[PDB]
Amino acid sequence: MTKQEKTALNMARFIRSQTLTLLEKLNELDADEQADICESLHDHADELYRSCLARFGDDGENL
Amino acid sequence: MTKQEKTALNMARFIRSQTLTLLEKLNELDADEQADICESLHDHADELYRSCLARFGDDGENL
């Protein structure tokens, strides 16, 4: 339906975004450390996302 | 100490709880696979909290 399915898909996609902006802020605080861990989180945020696309991959009914 | 440390810390802690709510709700939204990954993401997000508590040692969720 591309409805709620995308909503969940948006949440996972959103966390990835927070992790991106997190990377940023961490770099501001010379948090090299947290930055690495943040990119790993970035990927895993996508692990959630891509998988949310595996299920909610009905992104197409909306034209 | 500096509120920036606090904001960073809070975003890590945020993603942890956020992802928590996604594990359950996506599970409920029949997206258990995403729930699984949300569990790993749940604590991986917390890795930033841990590392932020290390580098910053800044906490104090209050106004």
Image: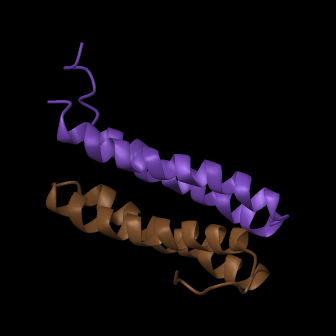
Chain colours: A purple, B brown
Looking at the image, how many numbered discs can be counted on the residues? 0
Above or below: residue A30 compared with residue A18: below
Of A32 and B34, nearer the camera is A32
Of B43 and B36, nearer the camera is B43
Of A56 and A4, nearer the camera is A4
Of B2 and A35, nearer the camera is B2
Most extreme residue toward the top is A63
Whether residue A6 is visible here, answered yes or no, is yes
**Residue at x 62% of width, y 48% of height:** A20
Q: Locate the N terminus of chain A by quadrant.
A: top left
Q: Locate the C terminus of chain A by quadrant.
A: top left
**Residue B17, image x and y in percent?**
40, 72
Above or below: residue B9 compared with residue A18: below
In this rendering, position of residue A8 left or right of residue A48? left
Whether residue B44 is visible here, answered yes or no, is no
**Residue at x 56% of width, y 66% of height:** B11
**Residue B48, image x and y in percent?**
63, 71
Task: Report which quarter residue B24 is drawn in.
Answer: bottom left
**Residue A50, image x and y in percent?**
42, 42
**Residue at x 44% of width, y 44% of height:** A13
Above or below: residue B49 compared with residue B36: below
Most extreme residue toward the right is A30
**Residue at x 80% of width, y 66% of height:** A31
**Residue B55, image x and y in percent?**
78, 80
In this rendering, position of residue A15 left or right of residue A20? left
